Amino acid sequence: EALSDSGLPPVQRVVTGHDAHGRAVFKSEDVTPTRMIPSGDASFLLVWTTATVPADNNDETDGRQREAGLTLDGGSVIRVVDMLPGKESPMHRTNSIDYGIVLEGEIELELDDGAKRTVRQGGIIVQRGTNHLWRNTTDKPCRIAFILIEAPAYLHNGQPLPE
Amino acid sequence: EALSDSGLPPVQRVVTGHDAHGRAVFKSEDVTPTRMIPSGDASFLLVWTTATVPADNNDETDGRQREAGLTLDGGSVIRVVDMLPGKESPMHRTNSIDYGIVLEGEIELELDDGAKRTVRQGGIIVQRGTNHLWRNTTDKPCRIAFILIEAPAYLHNGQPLPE
Ligand SMILES: [Cl-]
Ligand SMILES: [Cl-]
Image (cartoon, rainbow over all chains, first blue to last red; front, side):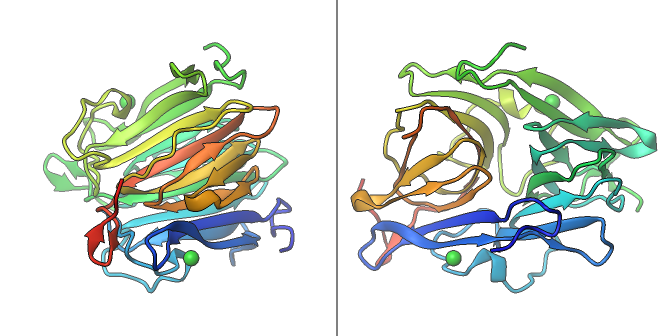
């Protein structure tokens, strides 16, 4: 419980579960800052993961503390990413569909060949396994919640794309 | 493009995809209001669905317009729900893990046997297949983005729970 390294508020996480009596109860609650990555471009927080999709509500593991699996981008991931002003992410593609929700500020999404657009605060991105980067061209941080869900490699003319 | 029935702004949706040349491009963009459900308790918007998890980035279907599947709560769903002031949702349990993100306002999450707590703006809920309702005990609407991901029925002493 400190301000995030981006200068934005820490994030409350509330996790539910079942007790020994099969009742729905609160499992954990915490308020935790996003923290700076080495590049200094973004401040982030992992919130949860599932080892598989479909998920397992009999898996009592804390998703924030789960050992690394096999399948790159296997299962699901929810994290919070604070893009810092004047910064951008590395361009890349993943084997997933991602739902991105702009919580605070706004963000420039750039795809292939210079294509780009702005996603305003409250906006949602459906990222369908596309090559992209995120760029903050504003003077304030932008917070985005990302949910990444396993999908096979995208098939172009029945084959994987070049990286 | 009108104000939502909750009085909150409409929601921008940006969807990515691949073109015939295997390039990452923008597939669609829209700004759409949440709309009132018959009960008058909430105003909602479906954003996307996947028929399965893992998902399929070769499935060009608009997730907002996908025909109903077999598996109740099969695949994934992202929707926006605006809980109206002084209103609450029906209590229920689903076969899913859900990530909920409070975009605006705050919300009371109630589980079994009267257990409840407040999730503040910017807060995240990890709902692990638990019986719950959402209650807005404030004088302003509360907007929550929900992502629901297929999971088997929760097993208590190796058996499904009573409904
Ligand atoms: Cl936990
Ligand atoms: Cl679409």
